[PDB]
Image (cartoon, grey):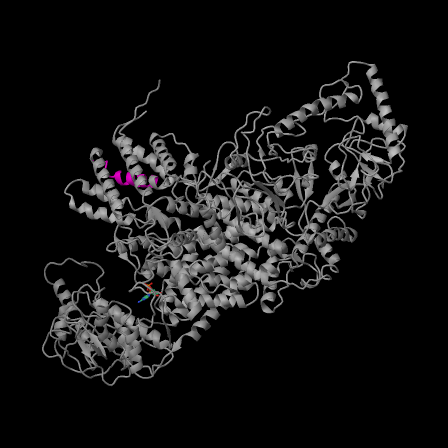
Amino acid sequence: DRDKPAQIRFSNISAAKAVADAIRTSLGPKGMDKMIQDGKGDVTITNDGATILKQMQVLHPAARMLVELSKAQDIEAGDGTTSVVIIAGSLLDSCTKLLQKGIHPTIISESFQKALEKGIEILTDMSRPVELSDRETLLNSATTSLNSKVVSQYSSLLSPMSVNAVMKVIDPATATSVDLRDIKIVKKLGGTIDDCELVEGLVLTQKVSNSGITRVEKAKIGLIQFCLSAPKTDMDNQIVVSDYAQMDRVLREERAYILNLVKQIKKTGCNVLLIQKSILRDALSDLALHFLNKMKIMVIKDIEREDIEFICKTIGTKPVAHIDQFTADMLGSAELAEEVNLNGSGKLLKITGCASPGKTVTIVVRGSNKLVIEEAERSIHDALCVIRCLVKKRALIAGGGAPEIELALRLTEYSRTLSGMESYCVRAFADAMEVIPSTLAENAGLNPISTVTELRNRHAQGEKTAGINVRKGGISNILEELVVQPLLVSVSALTLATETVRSILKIDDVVNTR
Amino acid sequence: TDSSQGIPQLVSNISACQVIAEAVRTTLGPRGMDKLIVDGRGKATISNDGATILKLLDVVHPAAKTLVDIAKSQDAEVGDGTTSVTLLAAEFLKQVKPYVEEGLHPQIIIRAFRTATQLAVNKIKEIAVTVKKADKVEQRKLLEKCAMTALSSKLISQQKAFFAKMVVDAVMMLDDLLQLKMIGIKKVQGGALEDSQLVAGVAFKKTFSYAGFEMQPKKYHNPKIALLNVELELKAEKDNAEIRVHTVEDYQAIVDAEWNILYDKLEKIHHSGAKVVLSKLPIGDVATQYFADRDMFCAGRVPEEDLKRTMMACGGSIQTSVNALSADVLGRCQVFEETQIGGERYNFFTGCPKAKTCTFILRGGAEQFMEETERSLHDAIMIVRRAIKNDSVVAGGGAIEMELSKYLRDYSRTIPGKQQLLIGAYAKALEIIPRQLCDNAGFDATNILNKLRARHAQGGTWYGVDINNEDIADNFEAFVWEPAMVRINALTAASEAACLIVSVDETIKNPR
Amino acid sequence: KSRLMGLEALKSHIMAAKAVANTMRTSLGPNGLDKMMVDKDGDVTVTNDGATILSMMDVDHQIAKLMVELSKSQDDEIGDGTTGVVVLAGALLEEAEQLLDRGIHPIRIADGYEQAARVAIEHLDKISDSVLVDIKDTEPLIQTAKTTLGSKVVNSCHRQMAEIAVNAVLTVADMERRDVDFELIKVEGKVGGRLEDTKLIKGVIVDKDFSHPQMPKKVEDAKIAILTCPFEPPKPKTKHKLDVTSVEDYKALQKYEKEKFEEMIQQIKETGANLAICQWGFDDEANHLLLQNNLPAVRWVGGPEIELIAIATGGRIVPRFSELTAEKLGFAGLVQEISFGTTKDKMLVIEQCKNSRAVTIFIRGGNKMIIEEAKRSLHDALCVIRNLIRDNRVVYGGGAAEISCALAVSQEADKCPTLEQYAMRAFADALEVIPMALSENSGMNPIQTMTEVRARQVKEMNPALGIDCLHKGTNDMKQQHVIETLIGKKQQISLATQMVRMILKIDDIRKPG
Ligand SMILES: Nc1ncnc2c1ncn2[C@@H]1O[C@H](COP(=O)(O)OP(=O)(O)O)[C@@H](O)[C@H]1O
């Protein structure tokens, strides 16, 4: 009937509001910390919203939908994964009082879609475009958008890695980017972090052997995937062992059995073999390794699946399996190998990979004490992420609360100008846009209502004036502070929030189960 | 069934005093909140003054009873400073509460409090500046500045301020007291052409008219108000009593027998000279005709306040007899006029031999403007009286407590004893006036107290607090001052109350 | 008894105010349903009045008593319209409690409502009309009467009573320097004929209440006379009875009364007097004897009524019985008896007066509710014509003034420190409750109609569009001849603002808890 769907909608709205209010005092650089307690008694201090959203667990359709929305927002854009929850909560709080009066959800959804389209068009018409066909303007935009993510010393430390990673000019200013398609940043322990340089081909870190000379050029990779494990017995001891007889049998089975397979395999050119991880093999027979020491020995272990996928994509080959194989589709490229250490500990080999169809290049970073390596990794990750976000479009704008107030005033004037019963619903959107500046003013340590009123008055008087400052603690113009953000991080977020609100509003009736 | 002596008794006394302290707190500033009080009868009254609230409330606690008695005595002996003393005592008790449970004998803090009070009194006496006829050439500029300061408290019209100055300057003749409770004031109702009028004499209210009321003369050369408690109404006199009903001649006989005595009495009371009869009971129908036939005056329905004002102005005497009167206990006027304005008839008794009361008619032609805008004129005339009578004066507001607190804090750093913390707490407890003044106006006292402390850290001027502009300005230039004698008495009363509260250690009860 | 400290007292007060205003919010407009009222006995009545219902209302709150007192004390200057002010105050208090939940002091909104009402009055003063002459107030008289009365007591129209009430005010307005007094016009009601028998008494009409209609009564007089001497054995305000200890004294007094009757008739026949009315009376036996023997004359004239008898003639009185002549009395013009029923008592209508100070109306009825509704409509017409002659300025009704004021408040609100725009937006949205309630009282959707009329008013000019409660053609206002006084609206707005300020000011603690 009508009471059951109304109660279901009220319960869903209450659950969504509780989920949104469980975390709210964390937006901005001056956010509060939270100590999450584990099930065993361990406590962990954190302040990121994504970690708290992915760590906690709760069974509810609205909570699962919000988690999926946050995950999609973090995957698509990559920044600002906490404002969408507040936007959805404000929209649901507005829809609550909209439905309390007696309005059909179809008109409310149409008004929300119209308001979203108007806000998107206003954000696109207000933002200013830039250029990026050359390298000077691109480097200027990079150094202008990179000096506002972390602290000053960390920024100065990551600037060399940033300008080394931004030099990867492969796509000639296309529509989309492939920064997540052919990038494999490895990590190496030991040495100095200053010894970093872009490396093509392939980089490994496992010792080949320990014999005489191993400086050859035979494809430098063994395309083999068949089983190399020893045939396991049916039980411990099949018979009674004491004197000879049984000793000679096992001796011949250990010496004159796998050696025949090694001989029949080594009859083909390019004697390069390897193996994957030693997660299922108990112990490898060293007699086979001693017999393989002659006529050139080359073996590399500790190989994962991602390494195989990277090698099969950079070179441009396909692995083969099975034993009955009389083809010749397993060779590679021969150029140069056999590398030594770079004045320090830790074995690491590099291959530049000359004359190869795949121009994939990675960055080999280092560090010490496992303290500046992960930080630099996260820094270059955020760097290439914001670089891809900037190269995806061309529009940019500054943050602080001014665009939110501008959009709220525009929606208010549009609802005042546009006629129809839906305009009231549009007015609800006008009351669901002044949450970020109020939260920022509350977290800064000033009066939020007075600051919001002053910002609204300044926007109504001189259009584009200033916003909300954090370092100084007042109202200063943003043009002096080097801080900007792309337009996609707002447009995509607003569209996703509107879609989630429409999906959670269109779902009602009864919730049957099995 | 449980009782103690010492620390628990003092804690209970402080907790009981905190109740009566928090009961009255918002009513301190000029725009305080209103309070509705009703008893078991069924009639409620709205009041905002602290004295009226404290008078209509009884507490069954000895400490609270002594506190309200001291407050009433201070309000009756002075007239200003009832809630401030209570707030100061409450703050002193709250500051002394944590310094009692730590094992401290309260017999050592009384001397420190007395020395601090003496130092504060000496500082106020050495910092007070008085001015009274020593500059500003002729007194014309002095009265001009006084009127400007009177009209500077409330933003009103110029004509109203001029009329208020005239009515406050035209009543300074034989008045030698320090309060306006002698002449008083009376608000009238109705409307007129002008905004306000002034006259010297006793006023009146609406009088009921009858047929032929214009027979009496409108102007009198030498009128004499007849002060007689008896009245001439149809219920007082009679034309037919207990008589045998037979014909119509007996009615005429008894009416003539009554009229003979009536005429004798009226001629005896009129031969003394009195001709303006002011009867308390309303007149009838034939009494007006009988008074107009004899060329006399008649009246009726008059309040007691008007009769008292007429007796005080004209100099009448209390007469407790109807007949056998003389010609010495009667009143003498000079000019009695009757002028109707709008829909009412007004009276004017001008020419009294004793210039005491004066009528300040304030009629604008409305029903809400008469009740409202009545406290501004009272505050203005009170400020005028305080500036005229008192000689010593100082800058008002929150500009005299911060300086004293800073001086006490600076002086407390030169004593090597246990009185250091006591003087520090006494100086800290003195900050309760500007914080409450800012909280009552709906502002942020935290953003103003810091600025006040920063300005008073090296300036030492008269920078107080503001309400309209919401900032910090000099109170000496805002034309707002206060006498330098009420604050000393208030501080002394607060110190005495605190000493009497801290001196009580236990109580003694007796069943029979 | 605990003391209400915190914000619970304000919440309880606002809840009580809303529960009180919910009773008046239902009955709004001419399409309102009849509200019933029953006391302790078996007296059940039905009516629709904002002052009669609020008078016999029982409440158990200190704020409700002050509210009903302020509502009853202000009713002589507005006439009809004591129901929308309660809804306006309730909506304002609801908006105040909604805006106060965020942590705002009530002093800010209380001071903002002052300038809100000020700018609303300033905008309403500029949107009106001032082109009324001696024709604009005389030709649309029938339209104004139809809009004031309506169709509640009688389905058909009434033009006689409206013109009579208009002339009764026109004959006193311009005669006393464009001024009128409330004590000059009186309302009289008595059952008898129909409602169309409306009479305008230029002089004074006085009833006598007879005892026996079968007694021979013949009219034959042409001159009135006023006297103060005892024309008959008087009654000095004392219930006389058989206080004589005799039996022959009764016959002696009867013979004396007969001789007094003979002497009185011989004096009024030898001097020229006729119907002499004094200020005394006797029992019914004396009147019966005086009507049976000869000359028709009825006593019983005690009370203050003699006052009018001292003003409907023209002269003075005599202090002594031995001071009568042919010139000390007063001449008359046409003083006789009038009785339209010819089966009840008689009435005396004075048709000779030098001034108009007791002009009244006489309307006949057939029940108790129809006459009450007729007298209420007459009082409303008198109030509206007084407001018209006091100021030649009106405005259109229906519900366009509130929308125009809200639009003006929303437009003239660009600059704001920190509370001005908040107060202006909390005061403007509370004004669109009257048209919404008026549209919901009928069988139409209020939200859609309100949005449509707001769009029509904001698109083009001419702010004269509203709703229609009679279900007609277009929603125009200048075609239906509907009008409303502006002084009444100003007084209602001022009263609502004062009540809201008084409610928002007194809200600390309470003594009885
Ligand atoms: N330098 C700065 N000046 C002003 N505001 C800032 C600055 N840096 C970040 N902010 C504000 O902080 C908000 C994001 O805070 P936070 O949630 O901690 O980061 P994220 O959204 O990337 O998780 C943004 O809305 C932005 O307005």
Which of the two residues, A478 or C237, is positioned nearer the viewer here?
Answer: C237
Q: How many marks?
A: 0
Main SS of residues in magenta: helix
Q: Which residues are magenta?
A: B86-102
**Residue at the farthest top position:** C246
For the C terminus of chain B, the quadrant is top left
Which quarter of the rendered image does ligand 1 occupy? bottom left
Which of the two residues, C181 or A1, is positioned nearer the viewer here?
Answer: C181
Residue A464 percent coordinates (x, y)? 40, 71
Task: Specify whether residue B444 is in view.
Answer: yes
Membership of B271 in magenta stretch: no
Q: Would you identify the image quadrant in which residue B100 lies?
A: top left
Residue C119 percent coordinates (x, y)? 53, 60
Which of the two residues, B119 or C363, is positioned nearer the viewer here?
Answer: B119
Task: Specify whether residue A182 is in view.
Answer: no
Which of the two residues, B41 or B455, is positioned nearer the viewer here?
Answer: B455
Is B179 on the left or on the right of C154, as rendered? left
Q: Would you identify the image quadrant in which residue C235 lies?
A: top right
Residue C108 percent coordinates (x, y)? 44, 53
Is B412 on the left or on the right of A91, as rendered? left
Q: Is residue B303 above or below residue C119?
A: above
Give the residue displayed 17% in from the left and 58% down from the top: A239
Residue C24 percent coordinates (x, y)? 60, 47
Membership of B101 in magenta stretch: yes
Q: Is residue A182 above or below residue B432?
A: below
Q: Is residue A227 above or below residue C232?
A: below
For the N terminus of chain B, the quadrant is top left
Q: Is residue A512 above or below residue C303?
A: below
